């Protein structure tokens, strides 16, 4: 099981999210109280990277999903049969991978040779104009409810900052629910 231990590191690495609210039309919304993102399948999911100092050239940013519950933590998070056989390929992402990155031609996908885990990595770039952070647009390609997949089992997304040689620079994580109505689901899970 990959580490989900938070680690800000030398560069003061922390995660952020748009303050999107919970309207019916929201694609992606983050709950600070739950540390949990609610998002629609295949829709854009802004995840912000915040640093106290800019990492060196050649830095990469990796994302991986693992199951939250200890009794599923060794099971590899992957797309359901129905979705992995869907005709939604972009030509880059393997069909079995839950998490894609949209709008980045330098995206890299990895099936771990030993753990069999899936992950997706992009070059870290410095903050764009108008932002104090760097935004990556993720897409989750399976619903949490999906049969033969997650089957309503909650997952975390682990975001690691690593240098060009593989060394760990930083790590954070947030819970995800991929669902039809993110705004409503967020309100409900906070209502408890
Ligand atoms: Zn699915």
Image: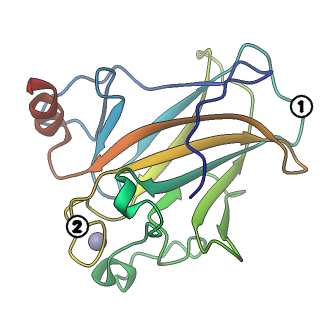
| Residue 102 visible in the shown view | no
- Left or right: residue 116 versus residue 88 is right
Q: Residues within 10 Å of mark 1 (few under 14, many from 20)?
A: few
Which label is found at residue 149?
Answer: none
Residue located 91% across and 50% down the image? 165
Q: Nearer the viewer, residue 133 or 73?
A: 73
Quarter of the picture containing the C terminus is: top left
Q: Nearer the viewer, residue 86 or 76?
A: 76
Q: Is mark 1 within 8 Å of ligand 1?
A: no
Look at the numbered disc 2 and give the secondary structure of its residue: loop
Q: Nearer the viewer, residue 136 or 114?
A: 114
Q: Which percent across, then down, holds residue 135?
A: 57, 33
Residue located 72% across and 56% down the image? 106
Residue tagged 2: 151
Residue tagged 1: 56
Q: Residues within 10 Å of mark 2 (few under 14, many from 20)?
A: few
- Left or right: residue 29 versus residue 170 is left
Look at the numbered disc 1 and give the secondary structure of its residue: loop
Q: Nearer the viewer, residue 120 or 2?
A: 2
- Relative to 190, does residue 182 appear above or below in the rendering? below
- Left or right: residue 161 versus residue 49 is right
């Amino acid at each position: 099981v990959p580490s989900q231990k938070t680690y800000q590191g030398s560069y003061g690495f922390r995660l952020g999210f748009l303050h999107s609210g919970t309207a019916k039309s929201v694609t992606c919304t983050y709950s600070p109280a739950l540390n949990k993102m609610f998002c629609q399948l295949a829709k854009t999911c802004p995840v912000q990277l915040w640093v106290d100092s800019t990492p060196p050239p050649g830095t990469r940013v990796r994302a991986m999903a693992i199951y939250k519950q200890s009794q599923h933590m060794t099971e590899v998070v992957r797309r359901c049969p129905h979705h992995e056989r869907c005709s939604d390929s972009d030509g880059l992402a393997p069909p079995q991978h839950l998490i894609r990155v949209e709008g980045n031609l330098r995206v890299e996908y990895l099936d771990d040779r030993n753990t069999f885990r899936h992950s997706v990595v992009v070059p870290y770039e410095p903050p764009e104009v108008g932002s104090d952070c760097t935004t990556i647009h993720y897409n989750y390609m399976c619903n949490s409810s999906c049969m033969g997949g997650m089957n309503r089992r909650p997952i975390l997304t682990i975001i690691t900052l690593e240098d060009s040689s593989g060394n760990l620079l930083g790590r954070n994580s947030f819970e995800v629910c991929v669902c039809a109505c993110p705004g409503r689901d967020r309100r409900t899970e906070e209502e408890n």
